[PDB]
Image (tube, rainbow over all chains, first blue to last red; front, side, top):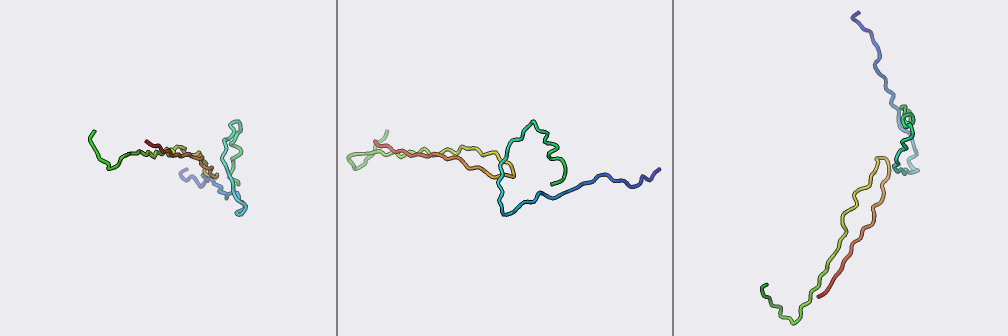
Length: 48
Length: 51
């Protein structure tokens, strides 16, 4: 056993961003996040 | 003190003094995807006196 045939190491999915209307206008303001919320599964996954 | 000469019979002193606005007002805390906020209103003032 010297050969050690082909395997896969890792896979990456890269999506796009959430689309939005150009002409309706943006308005954003930052806010502090609630510490009593498990914010991990709200941002989990590559999907838009 | 040494001596001077004016050719005039009265001497008046006018002192225009100004209290300008200090450059305080550090910077607001931002995050990269949001819009800014306006800067507060300052005050400057003048004053003048006579002797």
